[PDB]
Amino acid sequence: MRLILLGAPGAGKGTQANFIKEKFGIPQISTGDMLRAAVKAGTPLGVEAKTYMDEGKLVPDSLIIGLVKERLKEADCANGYLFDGFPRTIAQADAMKEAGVAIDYVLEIDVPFSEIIERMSGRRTHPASGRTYHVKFNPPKVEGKDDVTGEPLVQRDDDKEETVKKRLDVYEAQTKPLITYYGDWARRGAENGLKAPAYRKISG
């Protein structure tokens, strides 16, 4: 199993990642973890990456991909691997191809945006007790009040409908080019000696 896993924020990718990695005994690979491990281990690419990070600068694609190639050489990738939230751009996708990183499937977690927005933004809590409510699925008996105490209910700023929608929009514009990139390649055939990954919407 050699996988890219794509999922919108709030779509529950983290737990699905965990399910998939457990089932095939393949490691979850993300750029954050790769950078930190490489930096901590004083690897040559890690020291180089740190020169950018110390300065609040973008670590360049050339370097991330270099960390990827070393990462995939490790023992734990012998049965395969799961990219979580990488690639993010078509140039990264294309760098991975040109670097010879094999990918069998692009799996896109399938959970409609309206369900995500609905799920998160209707949430309310009573902070003193931790009691939760949902404006739709578990409404308080009196709007904006805790059933037990009568005290005010709150909504997290991160959960506000338009904050959530803005996160999905960004994800969407990041992800669509990646799906197109891989779909077009799969219709063209093998490149750099690699087959395009097969696209699956998994719901799943």
Image: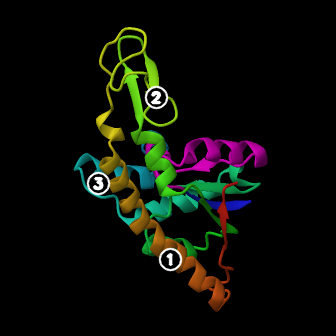
Q: What x and y, as percent, mark residue 9?
A: 46, 50
Instruction: Of the two numbered discs 1 and 2 on the same chain, state the one appearing first in sequence.
Output: 1
Residues rendered magenta in the picture: 7-36
User: On residue 139, which mark appears?
Assistant: 2
C-alpha separation, residue under disc 3 versus residue under disc 2: 48 Å
- Marks 1 and 2 close (CB-CB < 8 Å): no
Kindly report which numbered mark, 1 or 2, lies closer to the viewer in this rendering. Answer: 2
Instruction: Provide the residue designation for mark 3.
Output: 52
Q: Is residue 121 visible?
A: yes
Label 2, secondary structure: give it: loop
Q: In the displayed structure, would residue 148 be above or below residue 64?
A: above
Residue in view at x 64 percent, y 46 percent: 16
Quarter that holds the C terminus: bottom right
Amino acid tagged 1: Asp
Q: Which mark is residue 94?
A: 1
Give the image location of residue 163, x and y in percent: 31, 48
